[PDB]
Amino acid sequence: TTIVGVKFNNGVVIAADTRSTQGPIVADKNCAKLHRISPKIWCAGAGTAADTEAVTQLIGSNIELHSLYTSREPRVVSALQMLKQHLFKYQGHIGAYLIVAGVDPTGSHLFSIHAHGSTDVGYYLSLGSGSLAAMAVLESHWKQDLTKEEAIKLASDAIQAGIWNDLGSGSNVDVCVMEIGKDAEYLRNYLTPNVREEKQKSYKFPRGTTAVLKESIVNI
Amino acid sequence: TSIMAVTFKDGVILGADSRTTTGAYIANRVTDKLTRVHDKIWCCRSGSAADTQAIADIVQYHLELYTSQYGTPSTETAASVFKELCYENKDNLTAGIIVAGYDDKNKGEVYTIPLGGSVHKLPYAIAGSGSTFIYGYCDKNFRENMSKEETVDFIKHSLSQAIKWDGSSGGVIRMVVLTAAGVERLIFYPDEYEQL
Amino acid sequence: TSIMAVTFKDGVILGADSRTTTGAYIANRVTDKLTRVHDKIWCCRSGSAADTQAIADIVQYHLELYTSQYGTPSTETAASVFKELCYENKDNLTAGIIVAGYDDKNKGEVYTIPLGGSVHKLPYAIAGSGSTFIYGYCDKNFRENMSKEETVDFIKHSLSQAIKWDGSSGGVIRMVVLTAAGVERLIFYPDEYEQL
Amino acid sequence: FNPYGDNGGTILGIAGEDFAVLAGDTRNITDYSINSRYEPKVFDCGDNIVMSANGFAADGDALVKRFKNSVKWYHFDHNDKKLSINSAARNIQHLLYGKRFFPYYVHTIIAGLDEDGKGAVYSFDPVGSYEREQCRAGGAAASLIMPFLDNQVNFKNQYEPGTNGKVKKPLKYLSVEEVIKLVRDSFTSATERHIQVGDGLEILIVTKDGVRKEFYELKRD
Amino acid sequence: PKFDDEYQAQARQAPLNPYPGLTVTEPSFANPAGGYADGDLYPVGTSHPSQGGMIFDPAPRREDMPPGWMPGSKYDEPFGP
Amino acid sequence: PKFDDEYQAQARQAPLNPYPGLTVTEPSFANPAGGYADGDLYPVGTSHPSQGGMIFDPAPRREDMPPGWMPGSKYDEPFGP
Amino acid sequence: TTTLAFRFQGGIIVAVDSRATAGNWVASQTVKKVIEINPFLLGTMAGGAADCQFWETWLGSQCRLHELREKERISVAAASKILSNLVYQYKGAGLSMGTMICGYTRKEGPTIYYVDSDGTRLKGDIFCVGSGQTFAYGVLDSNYKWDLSVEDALYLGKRSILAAAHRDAYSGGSVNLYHVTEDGWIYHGNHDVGELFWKVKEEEGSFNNVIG
Amino acid sequence: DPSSINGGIVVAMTGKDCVAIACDLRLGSQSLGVSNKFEKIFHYGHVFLGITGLATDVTTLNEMFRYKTNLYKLKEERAIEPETFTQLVSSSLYERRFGPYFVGPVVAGINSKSGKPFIAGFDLIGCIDEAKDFIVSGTASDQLFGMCESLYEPNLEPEDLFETISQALLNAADRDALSGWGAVVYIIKKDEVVKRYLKMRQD
Amino acid sequence: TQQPIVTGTSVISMKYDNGVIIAADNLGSYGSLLRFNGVERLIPVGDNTVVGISGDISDMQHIERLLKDLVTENAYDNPLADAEEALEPSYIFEYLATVMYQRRSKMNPLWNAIIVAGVQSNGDQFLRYVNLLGVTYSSPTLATGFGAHMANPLLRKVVDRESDIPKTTVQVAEEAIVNAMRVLYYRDARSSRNFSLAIIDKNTGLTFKKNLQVENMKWDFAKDIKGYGT
Amino acid sequence: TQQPIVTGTSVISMKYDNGVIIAADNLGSYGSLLRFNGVERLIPVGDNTVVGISGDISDMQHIERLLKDLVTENAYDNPLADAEEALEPSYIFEYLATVMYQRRSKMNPLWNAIIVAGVQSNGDQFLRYVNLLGVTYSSPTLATGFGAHMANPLLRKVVDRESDIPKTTVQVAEEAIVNAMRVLYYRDARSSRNFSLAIIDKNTGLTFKKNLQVENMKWDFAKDIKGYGT
C-alpha cells in the first residue's frame, strides 16, 4: 500500500495506489483504497485491511448520525477524536493505520491515526509499505502553498514512486481533492500507467474439451 | 525525545524537540509535543504516544469539569489528576509526563511524573530518552530565579546538546513561556540552536 | 564506571572513579581502574573486569616484547594491539577500553575502543556507565590546548557529575597526568569534588 | 544469525524435439524492495548447456562458480571434450549433496540437448535429487506458471470434442516459436499476479545450431 | 540504547494460541499439565505414556507479529522497513 | 538503566542439559528433530503414534544458576544476597 | 508416497507411485521411485528423495566394486546391511529414507529387506512403505497369496498402489511396476492413476462411492 | 492449520452476462481423504456462496446464512441481492473479529434488476474483495490465480465460460495435494442455473 | 561478529554518463547514541575505485585493512602495477564478495553492506553491491540501509534504466546525490549533517569531496503545527 | 505493581530503653540512575508513630495517602481522638498489613517494605515489619533492603535480645543508627549521603531530624592502592 496526503494552499489532496495483495499474490488489481467518512472527509488505511474497513464504516455511520443530530457539517477533528478513542479502547488489537484528510468550516485538515490511538498533524503524510518511497518524493518536492495543480501532480508522483519502487504497491493511482470552497473531487484511476500486456494467443478451448459426468438444472 | 521545563523569575519555560521516531525512521520531524491542558497549565508528553495522548484528553476533560464546577485549577490539581490516571492504570500505561504551569500565588511550577507514576516538584525537569545526555549540563548550569532570556538560552543549549547526542531527538526546538503576561510560543531551527 | 581521558597542552590526563559494583552492592569502593601498560601509555578498563584484565596482561606482554625487539612503542601501537586482541575475540570478549599515552613526537594522544572493537582518535574520550550523563557537559566545556590546571578541573567537574548521577560510579576520583615531566598520580576525595 | 534469504526469482525449463528453452525473470528482490531490474539468472554455460540456480542469490552464485570450476577441471582432464547433459546433472547432484547438512537453498535447472539430440531439462532440489523432465518451472511463481504449462504443453485435462471424455487430445510437438509464445504468456501472467516477477524476461534457446538468447520486457511495477 | 518508538508501530506481541478463538489449540488445553498427585494415581506417573513432503523446499508466529495481525488475514505493513 | 557487574559475579549461565555429561538427557537427543521428508515416510507424518504423592509438599534450573554450578554439587554463594 | 513389494511363487512384485510433493504444491507427478542397483537388485525409495536417490546411487558403486573384486554379485542381505549401517551412522543428522532392497540371488532366492532412516533392517515377505502404506496393506493383506500367477500378482500390486493413491493425498501420480525374476528384474511399465482408476472401477465395479 | 486441514477449492468467473462458480468435492483431514461429496457451493435464492476453509465453519456459516437470508426474504418479501448478500456476509464475518471463522467465502450471482454479473471474495474476518473478472480461494489459491489469469478473458459466452472455468479448476486441482476427487461447476444465468460434475483424476 | 554495535547507516551511489558518484555520512552510531561523528566510510582503493561500507564499524576497519593489503600485495613483483595489471573495481569487488560469502558460510559474518564503485580500464562503469550474506547485484543506482528505500527512488527517478546513463551528466547526478543526502538526513534518525562524496570519472579520475554539509534544509513550515489533533 | 521502577533503597530502625529510632536516606533511584534526591520516606502518622517505607516510590505515596486518610477517618465522631482512642502504632501497622496482604492475594501487590515504629499509649515500644507479600515480624532491630544484611548486624551488636533494650540509651542507639547509615552509604550503591532520622520516645515524643549528613567518611586509605596485582 502507498498512501499520501498533501495539504496545499486551499485544501488537501489524498492519493493511493490500487494493488491489493494477499501474501505475494495480487488478489485484486484495482482495489479502491480511498474511503468516505463524509462528503468532505476521506481516509485511506493500512495494516489489517478488514479492521480498517470496519472502523471506517463505523466512524462514517456515527459521523453521519451526529451531523444529522447537530445539523452541522462534520469536523475532521470529530472523526479524529472518535476514531482514535475507538482505536485506543482495544489497545491496538484492531490494527488499523489511517491517513484521514478532509475539509470543514475550520479549514483543511490532514491527520494520521495509528492502531494504538496516537495521531499526528501533518502537511504531507505517507503510509503503507511504500511509505518511505513516497515520503522521499514528498520531502524532495513539497513546498508551502502549493497550487491545486501542483498538489495533485506532487501527490500523484509520490504514489507513482511508491508504485515503481515497492512490490506491495502497483497498478493505478487514485486521487481525491478536497478544497475549501467546494465539493470534493474523487479521481478514480487518475493515472493508469500499468496497462496490461497483450496475449500472444487466445487460449479459448474448443467447446467439448472438458469431460462432464453429469448435467442438471437447478430449481433456485 | 528531549523535553524540559525550567522555572524562572517571571514564570516557567517549557520546551521540547520536534522529532518523533518509529525505529530508525523519522515518521514525523516537526511534531509539537507541548500540550495545553489548561489556560496556564501545559503538560508535555514522553513515552507511548497513544498512552500520553489518551491521558492528556482525559486530563483535559477532568480539568475542564473542575474549572466549571470548582473554579480554576492549579498546576498541582492538574498533576494530581495525571497521577491518579497514570497510577490507577500503571500496568497498562507507559507514560512519563512533565506538567508545568503558572499560578499567580505560586508563580511558575513544574511537576515531573516519571514512568513509575510518582509526583515530584522540581525547579527544573528534563525527560525523554535524550535527557540522559544533559543531566550533567543542566545540573551544572541551572540557577534559581533566572531571567527570561537566560532561561531561554539555558533551555536552548540543553536541548541543543540533547539533540546532538540522541538519535531519537531532533528537529526544531519549540518552547512555551508561561508568565503573567501570557503564553508565548517560541521556535528555534537547527541552523540556529546547532551553532551555539 | 566513569572513565575519562583529556589531551591538553603539555600532554594527556587520564582519570577514573574508584567504585566497583556487583549489582547494587559496592564490592570494592577504592579500586584503581587505571593500568600502566607501558612507561608513558596507560589504559582504562571498562566493561567486564575479567576480560579487561586479561586483555591488559596480554597487551603488556606484547608491548614489552615489542619494546625489547623494536624499541619503544607509541600509543598507537598499544591501541592497535588492544584492537587486534579485542576484535579477534570480539564474540568472547566484552571489554571497552580507552588508551592514553604521551610520546614526544605526538605529545599526548587518546584512543578509545568501544565495545565493538573499533579504534578512534579523539581530543578527549569518556567511557563507562556514568559517561552517558556527562556527554553534554564535556562537549560544551572541552577546549583545545587547556593548561594542566584547567584540564584537571575539567576532569574533576565531569567525573563529579558522572558520580553524582550514576549509582555505579563513585568513590575517589583518580587521575594520572602524562607529560614530558613524568607521570603524576592525583587523587580527589568525595568531600573535595562533591562540594564543587 | 540467519544465514539464508530469498531473492524472489523464477525460472522455467521446457524441452521438446529439436530444442530446449530455459527462461527466467531478471528481477532481484530483498523483502519488498527491488534490488535491481536486470540481474540475469539464466546463464549460457558453454558446451551447449544452459544453467540457472534460482533461489537464494548468494548460494546460486556459489554453486554456479563451483560448477564452472568442476566443468573446467573436466575439460583440463578429459582433453577439452564436450560435457554431456547427464554428466553435468550428476556433477551438480554431487555438488549439492556435498553440503547435505548445510544446503544450497537454490532450485537449480540445467537444460540442453542429450546425447541423442533430444531436448533435456534436469531440475534439482536444494539437496540434490535431479529428475529429467519435459518441462519444469521453479522459484517464487512456480505454482502460478506450472499448471498452465501442463495444460498447454501436455494437454492435461483436455479431451477431443464429441468423444464425451473418452479420447484425450494427442500430444503433438510444439515448435520452438510456439514454446516462446507460451513462455511469454506464462511469464506475463506470473508478472501480473505475482509481485516478484515483473521486471524482465530472458530466454535462452538451446539447439544444435547453438545457444541463442532473447530478451523481453515485463511490467516492472 | 533503544530507538524510542513513540507510536508503538514497531510493537510486537503462556505462549500465544497460533489460531485464536479455537480452544482446541490453546496451549493450556492442549497441555493442561495434569494435577499435583498424578504420580500417585498412575503407575508410570503419567496418565498417557510433519507437513514436509518428499521434495525439500526453503506462516508467521503470532508472538513475532503485531497484535492487530490475524493469521491468514490480508495485512499491509503500515510503514514496512 | 542496569547496574554494572564488572566481576560478572551475577552473570548467569539451545536449552541446557539438566544433568551435564549424560547424553541420554541431551535436548537434541531426548527430542531429536524429525527428518525433512518424514511426512512422506510415515502416514501421519510422525515416526511414533511425575513426582509427589497424596501429600502436597509446599531443584534449581541450570539455565539461571552461575556457570560454575554443577547440579547436585556443594555450592556456597560467593557474594550473598 | 506409496511403495510395496511382496514375495510370491514367481518372484517379487515391486510397485510405487510417481507423485512428489512439497507442502500442498505437487512438485511433480513423474518421479521414478525405484533405483536400479543392478540387473538383479532393486531399491525402492520413499521419504526424502535426495537422501534415497544419492545414497542408493552410491550403493550402486559399492555393488560395482563388489563384483569387480569378488567376481560374484552382492547379496541382498549384504547390500541392505551396507545401506542400514550407512543410514544408521547418520541417525539424528536428518536423513529421511524408507527403502525396500528387493533382489534375487542363487543362494538366497527372492528376498526383500526393509531399511529406513532409524536404522532398522527387516527381512520379510510383504512390505508397504510411505505415507500411503496402510492403504496398500489393507488390500495386500486381504488379497495376497503365495501362489498368485504373475499376471495376478502384477494386478494386485497395481490395485494396492491404486487404493493408496485414491485415499492418500501424497500418493497419486502413476504406478510403476517391477517384477524381480529368477534371471533379473522386468519393468512392467508405467500406469497413470487418472486412467487406471477408471479402468479398475469399470472392470472390478469397486469404488462404488465415486461418482461416475 | 485450520484453513488448510480440510482443503478444498472455490473459483468464480464472470461471463458477458453470466457467472460461473466451481469447487472441488474432496473432504479430508490432511493426508486422509474422507468424503468425495462435500459440496462447498451453497445458494440462497439467486445468489451463490462458495466457502472454503475449516469444514465445521463451512457448515456453520451455511446454516447461519440460510437463517439470515430466509428472514431477509420473509420480512423484505424479496430475495437478497448479490451486493446486499456480500455486505451481510462481510458484517457477519467481522462480528467474530477476535474469534473468527476460518473460512474463505466467495459470493457469485447476478443482480436481478441490473442483470449485471457480480462476484466477491473475503478473508477470514470479512475484508470484501470485489473483482470484475474472477475470484479464487482455497488451498490451491495461487495455482488457480495463475491458471485463471492465463486463461480468462472478458465477455465469455456461457459455453466458453464453462470451458475456461472447468479447465482452470481441473488444472489447478491436479497440482494441489489436498484438492480433488471431482468438481462441480455452476453456470448461472438470469433465468436458469446449470450444475455440472467434472471428470478428473481421483488421486 | 553476531551483532553490530557501532554502525554507519547508509551509502548511496549512481552511475552517470562518464563515471560513478558515491556518498556516505560520517556518523557512526552506538545504538541510538550518535557517538562518533568523524568516521570515514568511503575507502579509495585507487584512482579508479572507491569502496563504500555500512554496518559494523569495526568490520569496516577490518575490510579497509584488507583493501590496503590487496593494494600492497598487488604491487609485489608487478612492474606494471601502476598503469596496467592494476587493481580494477571488478577485482576488488570479487575479492570482497568471496571473503564476505566465506565468512557467511563459517557462521562468522562481516555485518557490512559494501558498494564497490569505479570504472574499468575499458571505461565501463563498475557499480555493484554485496552484503553480509554474500548477495551481490548491479544496478544504475545502489543504496544501503535506509538509502535502499528513501534515497534509491530519488536516484532511480534520474536514471531508471541502462538507457538513461549516457543522458546523465556530472551535475545532474551530483544534484541527485545531494538531494538524496538531504532527504536521508530529514528522515533517517541514524544519519548526520556531514557527509563525504566521491566522484570517479573515466576522464578526470577520482575526486573525493570530504566533509560536505547538508544545506537548503526546509524547516520554516514547522511553526504552524500545533500538536496532535487540536 | 508487576515491577518497581523508582525505588527507595533501605530503612533501618531499632528500639532502645525508652523508644524507637528509625532512619532512611532521601534518594529515589530510577534503576542505576540516582534520579530523585529529595524524597521523604519516613512518614509520621502522629506523635507516637513513624512509618518507614521502601520499594516503589509511587506505591509509597499511595500508602502515605492511605495513612493520611486513616488519620482523617479516625478524627470523625471521636471527641477523644486527640488523647485516647488515637491511632496507636499497632492499629496503623495492622491496617497496612491487611492492605498489603489483600493486594498480594489479588495479584496486584504494593511493591513496598514497610517498618511501622512507635510506642503504644501504655509506653511499650512498637516495631514491626511488613513487605509486599504480607510477611510480618517484630524484632529489637529491623531493616529493609541492604539494611537487612549490612546494617542489621551492626544494630544487633547493640541489642541482640529483648533483655538488652533497657540497657540501651538514646545516645548509644542513635550512634549505632548513624554508623549503620554510614556503612550503608559505603557499601550500598543505591544509597545517598543525605538521610532523615526520627526518634519516638515514650517521654519526649516524636523528634524528626531531617536531611542529616553522613560524616566521618574514611577515604584517605585509598591513596595506597595502585592497581590490580602489581
Image: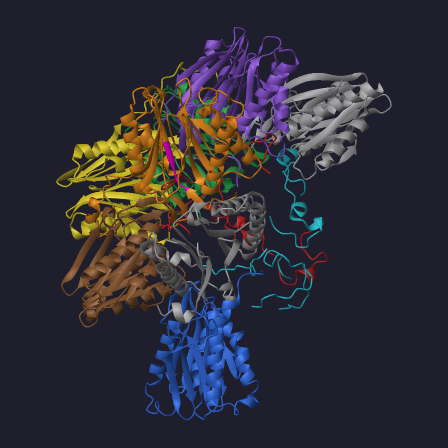
Chain colours: A yellow, B brown, D purple, E red, F cyan, H green, I orange, J blue
User: Residue I177 location in percent, x, y?
Assistant: 31, 32
Judged left or right of residue I58, residue A21 is: left
Q: Tell me if I can see residue H80 in this picture.
A: no
Q: Residue furthest right?
A: G107
User: Residue D41 location in percent, x, y?
Assistant: 48, 22
Residue D167 placement: quadrant: top right
Number of numbered discs on residues? 0
Front-most of residues B109 and I113: I113
State whether residue I118 is above or below residue I220: above
Q: Tell me if I can see residue F37 in this picture.
A: yes
State whether residue J13 is above or below residue J192: below
Judged left or right of residue B16, residue J178 is: right
Q: Residue furthest top?
A: D209
Residue I186 placement: quadrant: top left
User: Residue G150 location in percent, x, y?
Assistant: 77, 19
State whether residue H185 is above or below residue E26: above
Which secondary structure type mostly characterizes the magenta part of the structure?
strand
Q: Does D94 appear in magenta?
A: no
Over which residues does the magenta segment extend? Answer: I8-12
Front-most of residues G116 and A86: G116
User: Residue J96 location in percent, x, y?
Assistant: 44, 77
Judged left or right of residue I185, residue J141 is: right
Image point 70% across, 27% down: which residue? G55
Front-most of residues D211 and A105: D211
